Length: 129
Ligand SMILES: [Cl-]
Ligand SMILES: [Cl-]
Image (spheres, rainbow, N blue to C red):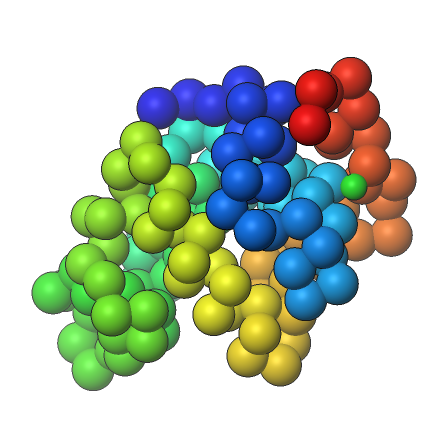
């Protein structure tokens, strides 16, 4: 599923991501656009043999199981296919665990390099939230 910008903002708000760990919803919309272009089915392979999955591009070396990242953790306790669903609940729940692990949203490179220090609220502007 390829989300609309205000559609995703609304679905993130429903799932408790607005102001979660002090991050306003713009930051979530922003890191979704530049990681996955709002496509829940985005996958990308990393150099080390791990894979990023879903609308936030969550990494198999630490958070999910794809059965092909030898010696990786499953700290969100989910198969990585579950992040590719049209229902973002699994992605949101894992993302709450990630952002709370100490390093904030800097875990997401594309948030660090393309959203942080920006007027992130522009990403929710015009939306009925
Ligand atoms: Cl915002
Ligand atoms: Cl980047």
